[PDB]
Each structure stands twice: as structure tokens, then as C-alpha cells.
Image (tube, rainbow, N blue to C red):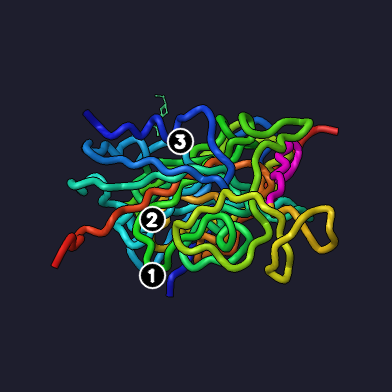
Amino acid sequence: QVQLQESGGGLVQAGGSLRLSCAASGRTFSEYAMGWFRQAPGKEREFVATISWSGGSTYYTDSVKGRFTISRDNAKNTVYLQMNSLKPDDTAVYYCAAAGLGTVVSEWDYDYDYWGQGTQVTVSSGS
Amino acid sequence: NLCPFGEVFNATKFPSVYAWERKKISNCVADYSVLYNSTFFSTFKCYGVSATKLNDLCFSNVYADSFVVKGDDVRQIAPGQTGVIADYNYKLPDDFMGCVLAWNTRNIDATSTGNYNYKYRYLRHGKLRPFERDISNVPFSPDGKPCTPPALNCYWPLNDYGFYTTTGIGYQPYRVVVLSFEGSLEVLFQ
Ligand SMILES: *[C@@H]1O[C@H](CO)[C@@H](O)[C@H](O)[C@H]1NC(C)=O
């Protein structure tokens, strides 16, 4: 009933950019917090960024602080993730996620009730 | 004059969770702008009260509690939660109305060698009640009777958090602030 879907991932190389998108359905999108998670291969899924229902307050993980930008479009029912200056570490499947009632922001995977399937992002470099 | 929230959130020193401290905020009108849109906060959940609407409130009688816990223990600062923190250190009522705020303090509360100044209680006879606080440090026995070390089956109930800068986020230090809102209608006498 209430579902997310990722888009905008692909192949890029180190120093390029990528603009992720995630459309939601099932209820009012402007009433909940959203958050981005990612999972490198082998390593456990970690948190990236989170946006409040209003877009006013945000918070990011340190590995991306300064490079990544989370923003939403409540008119468009979708939240984005601008990624600049990508590094081979940033290779991961990126999961979109939606928070629950009363959650303004959260970096914690247990505070989001709905999860998308994930879009691949691969940054490759020289060796 | 507006409620002095900066002196709570931006205070230099914070306490151990077992010795959590409480500030009354009243006789002021509160500008919630500083909490609403920020890059400062990693966790922000409100319970019972509308998370959107706190700037509307007009007759403020709020209590702010401060303490430090480990990242994985932030989960326990919620109504109806179990665990060493909720049971023995800081317990939130089922009927809680208010907000729970926390932010990572690794760069100021953790060291490469390890910061062991922050403590939590881990042995106790029976769970705390909501908003109960226990700063006693007396030897504990699993059968309830009094107790004098170095007797067998006699333990000390506090233990150190150990905050290193190399551990995962779940073990990094977090400063927490709980805002509790008094009931809106209180009967003083009949
Ligand atoms: C702490 O102080 C800084 C500088 O004025 C400010 O950006 C921040 O919002 C303050 N925090 C609170 C809760 O007032």
C-alpha cells in the first residue's frame, strides 16, 4: 500500500556527480521524515542523510559531510540526494526510507517503517 | 525574554545518565526555531504532543533533562522501553508527552585513548519509576540484603562508559535532552 522506489543511480567515476530520486505513495508524503541509507558489499547497511517533513532540518553522516545534499519536493512527492565528488568508497546500494509518526529526524534504521528496494551506485577509479 | 534553551543544549559539561539533571523552563515564552530547523540534531522524536506544533504552545511549564549515553542506548530513551538504561537509569512514562533529542558528541566527548568519565548504573533491585533518579552508590547483593565488601556476592552497581574515537557509531557518545511537558489542567484543590 505504502511504497518507495529508487532511481537515478548508475555508473560514474571518481569526482563526478549523481542525483538520486525516490518517489513515495500510500499516504501524505509531506507528513513524514525521509532518510537515505546505503550498503557497501559485504559491510552492513549504514545511514547517510535524513530530512524532516518540512525540509528545514537535515543531518548527514560524516563520510559525506560537505559533498552530499538532501532535499525534498513535497509538491512532487519525492526526496532527492545530490552527490558530488564521489569516491570509490561511495559504492553501495542506496536505500530510500520513510519515518513514522512523531519522528522529526533520525539517523537510526529502526525508526523508519518503510524501505525501498535500492538502486545501485558504482564509482570506479584507477589502479 | 525568551526561554534560555541555549544554556541547556549548548552547556559545556553534561552529566552521566544515572545522575541525569533537570532544568525547569518557565516564566518565558519559548522560541522553538532553534530545534525545528537545524543541522545540529541527529535524533528528534516527539511523543503524545504534535511534533509540528510546539511553537504554538503558550503557557510553558517544561522540564529539560540532560545526560550522555552510548549510541545504541538512545533507543531506550522512549516510552515503554526495556533495558539497563530504561530500567535502572532513566525511565520514561508510558503516558509521556514531550520530545527526545540526541546528537553525536564523538569529537568532544570521546578520545583516542578512551573517555571513561561517563557512568551508568547496571545493578539494581527493581526498575526505576518514570522520572525517578538514583544517585546512590552502595554495594549490591543479588538477594537484597545489606552488604559490605570484600564479602562474596557483593558488587558495585555503577560502571563506566568507554568512549573511543575508533569504534562504531553505536558505541560513540551521544548528548541527550528530554523535554517533558506538564499536564495542561492541574487541580490544586477540590
Ligand atoms: C548553540 O549555539 C549556536 C551558536 O549560537 C547555535 O547555532 C545553536 O542553535 C545553539 N543551540 C541551541 C539549542 O540554542
Count of number-bearing discs: 3
Marks 1 and 2 sit apart, C-alpha to C-alpha, by 23 Å
Image point (71%, 55%), residue name: B139
Q: Position of residue B47 (x, y in %)?
A: 38, 60
Mark 1 lies on residue: A26
Element type at mark 1? loop
Left or right of B56 on screen, residue A13: right
Q: Amino acid at mark 3?
A: Thr
Residue A124 vertical position relative to residue A10 in the rendered view, above or below:
above
- Going by the picture, which residue comes out furthest to the left? B190
Q: Are marks 1 and 2 on the same chain?
A: no
Element type at mark 2? strand
- Which chain's residue wears label 3? B
Q: Local crowd at mark 2 within 10 Å, few (<14), some, or many (≥20)?
A: many
Q: Position of residue A80 (x, y in %)?
A: 47, 47
Mark 2 lies on residue: B46
Marks 3 and 2 sit apart, C-alpha to C-alpha, by 18 Å
The foreground one among B107 and B137 is: B137
- Going by the picture, which residue comes out furthest to the bottom? A1
Question: Earlier along the polypeptide chain: callout 3 or callout 2?
Answer: 3
| Image: magenta residue range | B158-168
